[PDB]
Image (cartoon, rainbow, N blue to C red; front, side, top):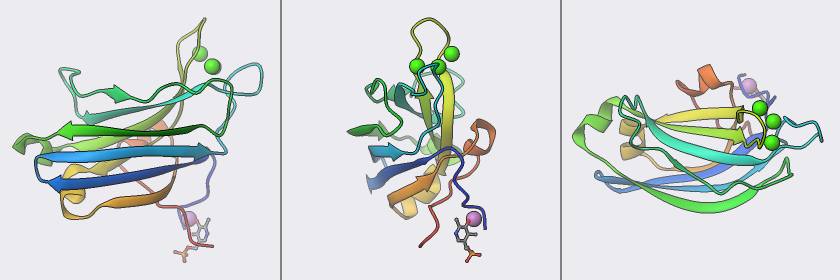
Length: 142
Ligand SMILES: *Cc1c(COP(=O)(O)O)cnc(C)c1O
Ligand SMILES: [Ca+2]
Ligand SMILES: [Ca+2]
Ligand SMILES: [Ca+2]
Ligand SMILES: [Co+2]
C-alpha cells in the first residue's frame, strides 16, 4: 500500500531511555542498488537531526566496501534538547566514492517527538532522498 521496495531495506532499532537521549542501532541493509561501475556500492549510513542549520549533529557508520548487503551493527547516541521536538532523525544510506562525490542510495526519517513516545525495532523500506526527510515505511508483513 506504500511498501514496494525499490532501493532495499534497512534494519534499525531506536529507543529513548529518557527524553534527553535517543539510542540508535544501525543493523544491516539488504538488496541495495548498485552505484559503481563494478555493479556494487560502498555503503555507509549518515545520521542527523534535521533541520541542522549549523551542521552539528551528523554521525555515521563505517563504510563497508564492495557490497549491496552491508552489516554495520553500530550504536549511536544523540543527546537531545527541548528544541528537538521540532526535529526529525534523518537516516540516509550513501555509496562512498573515491574519485567522485558520494552517491545517495536511500533514506527515511523519524519524528523525534514520536521516538520519545514509542521505540523502533525492525526492517524499513528505503525511500528517495526527498521522501526520506518526511517519512518512514516499515516493511510490509508477508
Ligand atoms: C500495500 C502492501 C501490502 C498490503 O498492505 P495493506 O495495507 O494491507 O493494503 C502487502 N505487501 C506490500 C509490499 C505492500 O506495499
Ligand atoms: Ca558510486
Ligand atoms: Ca562507491
Ligand atoms: Ca559519485
Ligand atoms: Co505498500
